[PDB]
Image (cartoon, rainbow over all chains, first blue to last red; front, side, top):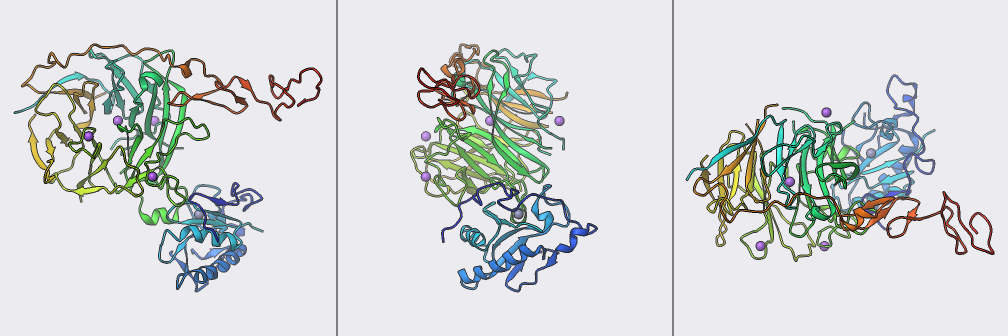
Length: 145
Length: 421
Ligand code: NA
Ligand code: NA
Ligand code: NA
Ligand code: NA
Ligand SMILES: [Zn+2]
């Protein structure tokens, strides 16, 4: 397994193309009926920084599959989620974080060096779009219903 | 013992800083907070028409560091007429933008706004600790000092599209013959040819820097350039040293010492002027109340000594001759520092004023359907090729000795026919 380069993303296309995570339908709030597709992820093998556990199923799957890949990769190191669904603001419009289809992740030890390989693991985990967004975190996302 | 100041111009509109371009014209360009750059003749008069005017693009404010931040002329502006400006804009509180412009090839005293070419667009969450000071080094590369913008780690750890450039110094080679990119990265750079780090980053450790003094003639032999900054966040000063003939493999460390005493501090500078012989080589820093002081290290021991300098401040300036200026607060005016011990303009400081002339470079001359790099290369826009982008390029491209002329109209010589021959 070869790590992802800084500021590199897979697939090598725009996130909201059909090849990646697909188009963006709209922001998901609570008074919006579509809020029912979002459900908490109580995986004990994942660290939530912190309603940060709410997310779509395809996201839950890909994320749960990744949680294993991490501790399988490093000794006693878990998968850490810094941001998931955004209940309001904190993001630019049309961000998949508004649809619970996106997640920002790091390792438990905050070892920025591992981040490169982490992204790769997320790619093989089946994430529809992974992106080495910055030194501080990786951004992953999936498609919807 | 004491220094004196003489007024030069009033009625200024929220000045922030002033500088020259090194082209003989001895024009003093004055940056204004709200997005204007006015010119001051060597005589002392202000032009009617602004050199630059982008008050619409720049979103400033009073208090709040937003607005026109800094501007730096290319070392060869006399030939290429290239300049670089940093400012805040918006539509996330705002954006710190760094762009390259080019003076009108018709009028040397005004820039062609169409020649805008964006290099960096830094995301900003707040309106403090922005920085944005532009400057060139003896190496020729462009430096960019950026404050931390108060972007905590948590912020950058749970937010997308954040700078990742804030709180550090950047190194960009603007002299490139490459077209696919706005600029290139020096091999000297630490993170050059890297796969895990931003090649632009030269060093980090900044927070809320004022105007950093740039000593271009360090008293050292190995150190060819040194930059001294004053932070306030606590409060201290940090300086970055640089060697010309050195290929960095790692990050240059910022020296964090504490020379100053207690109070705040607007900024500083190193006197390179001719007017004063005693002030020569001395670092000078002042605060918003006109309280100044001088700094000086030592070849041996390398200790710093602080001596008070006898005499609302908004910024400083430096003409071609090296003479420093003060900008205070249409209330706003420019002053000039003068050493009473010597004449205002000694017989040796005299200099013939060569007026700014039109760009006569080869690129500025015959370069169409593209732009000129600071090195003179004409980067063709899509649909063009050849030295100066005159050779039309079809889609699909012409085959069998086919020559493109009209929009995608190939041209097959005798014996051939078809859309692409
Ligand atoms: Na404005
Ligand atoms: Na400058
Ligand atoms: Na290097
Ligand atoms: Na030197
Ligand atoms: Zn994200």
